[PDB]
Amino acid sequence: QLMNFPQLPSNGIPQDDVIEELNKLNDLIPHTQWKEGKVSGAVYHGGDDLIHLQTIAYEKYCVANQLHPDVFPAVRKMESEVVSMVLRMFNAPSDTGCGTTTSGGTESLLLACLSAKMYALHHRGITEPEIIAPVTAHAGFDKAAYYFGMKLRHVELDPTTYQVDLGKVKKFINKNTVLLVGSAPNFPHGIADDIEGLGKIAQKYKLPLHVDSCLGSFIVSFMEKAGYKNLPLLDFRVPGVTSISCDTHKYGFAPKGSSVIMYRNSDLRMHQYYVNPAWTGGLYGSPTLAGSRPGAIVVGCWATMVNMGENGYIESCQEIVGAAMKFKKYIQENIPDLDIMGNPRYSVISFSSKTLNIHELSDRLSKKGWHFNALQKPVALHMAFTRLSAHVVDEICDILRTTVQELKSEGVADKLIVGFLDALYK
Amino acid sequence: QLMNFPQLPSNGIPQDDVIEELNKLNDLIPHTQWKEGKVSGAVYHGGDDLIHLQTIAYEKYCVANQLHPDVFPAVRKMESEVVSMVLRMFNAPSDTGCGTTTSGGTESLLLACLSAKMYALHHRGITEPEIIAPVTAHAGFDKAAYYFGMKLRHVELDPTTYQVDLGKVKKFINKNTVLLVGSAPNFPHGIADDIEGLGKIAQKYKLPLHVDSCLGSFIVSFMEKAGYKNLPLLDFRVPGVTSISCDTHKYGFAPKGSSVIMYRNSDLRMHQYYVNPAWTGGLYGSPTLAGSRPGAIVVGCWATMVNMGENGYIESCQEIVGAAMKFKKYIQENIPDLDIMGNPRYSVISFSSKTLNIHELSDRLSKKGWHFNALQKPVALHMAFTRLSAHVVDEICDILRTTVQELKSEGVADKLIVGFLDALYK
């Protein structure tokens, strides 16, 4: 049995008695087997070898804190490089094309939102900021409206392609609209909204255009280098594109808790910064929303991108997307009871069904240890393909079986969410 | 010479060619010698042995993501423990006394602010939130007002004790006031504001009381167990105390990027959470402000607190504070040209001088490789004692020498800060 600690021990336990417990924890208390590619997301690589790299890199820069460039210059140099490499993947202006680093993919979105808020509030003085984005967007956009007190307006989609209706959005352009969003790809259905034709509308109403490539990251960019044709534009080559998010801790396989927000020029990110010279403790200047920052993490991110190179994320994209498509084809050819959502061109595959109760089906799967992300409006579920789940041949026959087992069988919910949040500390 | 990367390499370089570069970086590009205890802050421990622990712990839980408790349960169990141990250090109600974990010490402050904003906006419906705090507070409080659009009102201090004037604050109690802050200790001067007598005023105007112990962390709490007398109350034993911040990545020696925010009951933190069931991608529920979170970091934090135990942070407090006091005494007995700021009872020591130009003095030191935090209003400087700088006997004779070398010698600055922020990516 493993020992728990309601409070600090009388005497500190040796390092040896610790790692033993660090293993007792992994070995004992059961969990979802991500190592066996049974989770849609969470772990995106899992390679014992890769982990070891970012582990020793962690050790080298364990104390690193981006708050102090004068003390940790190498970390500064490695960030300027990371952002630089990511900028080239999305073909940002080699001239004014700047960028910045963030923690989670969520912080990246909030910084693009704060950028537009304090921008339109500087060139238009909008006292009532208003952000508009697809319903298929990410909760990261729904947070910004809550925190910054902005007005978030959801826009419905095209029932056929499941993309975004570029017409309904026009009906929402106001004197308060500060930015328009285009998830590419979105989290729910993994389908890139019309971006190539969205960099034209942005130019019309002089509004900032943000692309939520947090999920796409190192897949969408390499779709072209992987040898895939008929692919829209999802980046700065689209003149109407302002900012672009990208999670390196996702499909970059970088240490969890590392993403990047990009811009077309510096005067934009200027509005995402915080400046307070008046402060007595000195004169703060957070490039992001955080004070002290985990230097090691970004270093581990820098090391993976080099160890992988441009050739790595190709053999990565080809593999991941390769499986996602094989998956899609199998649930079309076989498993006739399922319905693909739109035309997933990438590594994320979504689907639904009116013949079966998808809600119960999900439970039938989770009971077998396989966890698909449960969706709503419409009620569905998907599988974000990772290197681990890239061993798909198994869970294709698995889902068919489960579907075979299905057909062979004759109020304010706001208060509930808070409950399982408090339950994370007992 | 070290190789730089404007973009991803043609072919990924072997792990071996990476760690070599990871060392070339440390070895080559010069930096401030924190290992020699020449930095007031940044690195708080630096122990090769300790680092190794949190390094292998990192490896065990490298993929860990707090977004998925069902996948990483051990991380859940270790967080519930961490918060639990920290709660006991500050003597929170063993009944309703709850808590939560955060990234940087900054996020912890913002969550206490959002807590009060969405609280007074729920029980009083205050459309114009108003936060009041000492000028000696932290920039973390100045950020919340900027992001959440709250009104931050600074309050001056007592010219003699350098604490906070509990009278001037009374003159600011409004129908918009949502919380009062009490830095303990503050960053600028490392002097704990009157908290023992501040838990009485909080009860008067039924306002939430937040203690910024982000800097004090594992020092203030252990001041009593270290064998020190005549110590005010800086925690929940003060009935008027609502929330309390604490940076574990500071004096806890935990992996950088880990702090904790505490409450007296759950209904408080309830307001710091984010809830969005309406979201189509599912039903988000961020306990903090972040999406995906670095599980490894909190695990490394959990491992240090156990390896240290309650006996570790005593031999820690006794050592750190021991040096800070020896430092203070030496600049009083010797170095008659300096003036201690108030009565620093802890590990942080601040001072000033009218005889010498402190600004130039700071430069004289930084030129010798010794970096003290430059302060303003009043123009001064301090030294936050870490385990490394806890070898003080040296830099006491160093500062005297530098002072000896001193006396032996016959517009909108807002636009400037943004400059050195953009310069972090070239």
Image: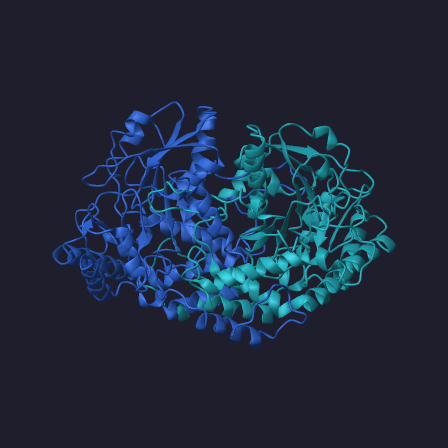
Chain colours: A cyan, B blue
Nearest the eye: B99 or A199: A199
Nearest the eye: B111 or B134: B134
Residue A117 location in percent, x, y?
57, 36
Quadrant assignment for the C terminus of chain B: bottom right
Give the side of residue A273 with respect to residue A323, left or right.
Answer: left
Residue B313 seen by the camera: no
- Residue, x 47% and y 27% (percent of image)? B121
Nearest the eye: B412 or A165: B412
Residue A336 seen by the camera: yes
Give the side of residue A89 with respect to residue A267, left or right.
Answer: right
- Residue, x 66% and y 28% (percent of image)? A174
Give the side of residue B179 with respect to residue A206, left or right.
Answer: left
Looking at the rendering, which quadrant does residue A62 occupy? bottom left
Which residue is most to the front?
B410
- Residue, x 55% and y 47% (percent of image)? A107
Give the side of residue B369 with respect to residue B61, left or right.
Answer: left
Residue B83 location in percent, x, y?
41, 50
Residue A286 location in percent, x, y?
46, 48
Nearest the eye: A280 or A423: A280
Residue A18 location in percent, x, y?
42, 66
Q: Relative to residue A232, is residue A45 depicted above or below?
A: below
